[PDB]
Image: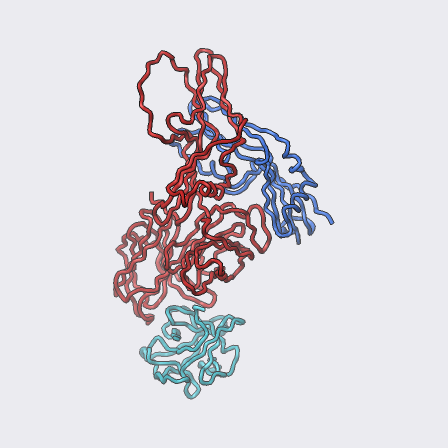
Chain colours: A blue, B red, C cyan
Amino acid sequence: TIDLADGNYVVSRGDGWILSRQNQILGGSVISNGSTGIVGDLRVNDNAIPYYYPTPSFNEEYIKNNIQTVFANFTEANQIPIGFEFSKTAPSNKNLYMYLQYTYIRYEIIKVLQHEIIERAVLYVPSLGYVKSIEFNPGEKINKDFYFLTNDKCILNEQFLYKKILE
Amino acid sequence: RVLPYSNGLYVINKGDGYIRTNDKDLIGTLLIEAGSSGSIIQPRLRNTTRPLFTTSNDAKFSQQYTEERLKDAFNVQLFNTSTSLFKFVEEAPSNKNICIKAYNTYEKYELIDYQNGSIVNKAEYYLPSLGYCEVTNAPSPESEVVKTQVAEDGFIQNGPEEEIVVGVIDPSENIQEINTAISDNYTYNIPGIVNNNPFYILFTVNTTGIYKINAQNNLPSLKIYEAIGSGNRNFQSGNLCDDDIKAINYITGFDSPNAKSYLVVLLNKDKNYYIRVPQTSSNIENQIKFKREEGDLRNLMNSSVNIIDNLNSTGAHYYTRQSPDVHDYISYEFTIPGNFNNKDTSNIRLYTSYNQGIGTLFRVTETIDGYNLINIQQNLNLLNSTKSIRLLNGAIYILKVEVTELNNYNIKLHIDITN
Amino acid sequence: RTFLPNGNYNIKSIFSGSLYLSPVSGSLTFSNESSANNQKWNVEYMAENRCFKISNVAEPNKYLSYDNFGFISLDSLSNRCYWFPIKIAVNTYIMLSLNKVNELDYAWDIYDTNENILSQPLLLLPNFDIYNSNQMFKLEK
């Protein structure tokens, strides 16, 4: 129940979103005893793919057009490659595991009626990445929460940046 | 060790950092003179990478398929091409040389047909990962050489211990969907096109609560599954949205053919659920009734209520069913042989042979609104229970069993009646 | 469905099979099976009041009801002719009047000298729980 005038709004939640079940897809490297690991990535037109969750009334096109008019235009931008990498050094006693996960911006577009949200379509367009380190002795049981994101989330704080879709 | 799992397809992530024996996977060792530093880089000048795959059945569990199941389970994008890159770097101390060696690695996925107590099919998919590196003191080059025999082909895990399982929609079972969110009641007709095969029903609900779901005449027996991570992302009030999720989590339900059952489950508005109607067999038309239960029946929450119509006037009876896991529930609605005097009684001991449980006993009264459970006995300890109770002939009761210790895949319930 | 499906039922006391609900000199009493339409009750869920009405098949414009003396009655249709059944075992029910008397429910009840009801009129009397034998009646087919 959100305090806005009846109508359609375009909305940016954060950079820094990450998706259910998708930790570990890219693989992960394991490094031991105070050597250093550096995993990183690029961006042709795989990383580049955005994920659309449309609704009746908010078709893919509608979404794309409408958020590219307000915010970061992505189709244009993710043609030029950009890189990112992380550099984790291990302690000397034990060894550690680090794996790469792609971060996304969460755009969504919302129908409001009666200070209430009746409908929401969502677009995740890929930003950069994020790595998670963990130190382990072999046999040491690990928290399932570490390897499995069970519900989408932002690893940064969210936000709610909005614009009314015009008539 | 019991590993109850409501039979079907499961893909597991058995962990990262796997390598093959005999350095089939070593990139190479390089040796760092004290006070220098040295790295080994996988730059991805060329994308292509090789996964490794082995299966019990090519015909069923083909690499293409067992790849698709990883898409289903973890939405894995790429299988033999990574643009993601890795390097290992090390500095040697000034006293002694150091030497760093690097192995390519794999995440190890397992794909499983787990039908009815045992894995009837299994594939192992080794997905190319992002490295393992060992740093050691430089070995003395004069050190003597041990004639040493190579090892059996196989694998070593260097990543931390991991095993995380994910249920997946069986691509051979169709999906049918209910576009309208279920509200308070709803009756669903099994369409033509399912042709009495198994299939899935995707649906959602509007306001969150407890629902009784049965088929026509509580037959066939159903299972319900939550879809993992549903209902963040898109939503349209009143209807469902596809979300794009075929990774599923078993809530409750039997796999047994021709057992009579109804499900009683909690359902949350911000999630999507699949139901799995099994092979119909029958040529008559069937239906799935969803009712929202606001009454006493919430007591059976996240249980499948098993139906026993068939008691003999006296004697031993038993009812073997897939056991739920520790701290989940199986329930049992039974009506006791004999006409209802309201003074007549039959003596009823309720044992269980293999697993322990907390049994909860109710008398059932039914009104036009719904069941009413009157509370008869609590805290009953079932495992080989000496105990008995006098129940009323012709009256109808429900036993709700919480599994406490899980000692066997099936839970066998006895109703041994005396007079 | 499943629960009291519309149709043609017999109506007994749990105190004796071999006796059926029948109207006689304008009272309702349990009597010897006559295999006739006098003893067959047509019971009809009326979804508008979530309750059931029960007509006598041989005089099917007359429904089961009650008067301002204690008795259950056969009468032309009235809000009194509405009943809210509670099933408490295969085929047995405790018929409550939908509309409550003061703050408490009433039910079909029938007196027994010793589990014997032979000449007894069916009356409407306060209900409390599901444990009153006399309040219990069974409806078959």
Count of marks overlaid on the render: 0
Indicate the quadrant where residue A135 lies: top left
> Could one spot residue A84 in this view of the protein?
yes
In the picture as drawn, the residue positioned furthest to the right comes out as A167
Front in this rendered view, residue B92 or B50: B50
Q: Is residue B24 above or below residue B355?
A: above
Q: Is A9 on the left-hand or right-hand side of B341?
A: right
In the picture as drawn, the residue positioned furthest to the bottom comes out as C25
> Could one spot residue B300 in this view of the protein?
no
In the picture as drawn, the residue positioned furthest to the front comes out as B59
Q: Is B236 on the left-hand or right-hand side of B119?
A: right
Indicate the quadrant where residue B400 lies: bottom left
Where residue B39 appears, as percent x and y from the top left, is 50, 20
Q: In this view, does B93 lie above or below B311?
A: above
Where residue A136 appears, as percent x and y from the top left, is 42, 29
Question: Residue at left 67%, top 42%?
Answer: A67
Front in this rendered view, residue B333 or C25: B333
Q: In this view, does A66 lie above or below C36?
A: above
Where residue B309 appears, as percent x and y from the top left, is 35, 64
Front in this rendered view, residue A128 or B373: A128
Where residue B193 appears, as percent x and y from the top left, is 49, 58
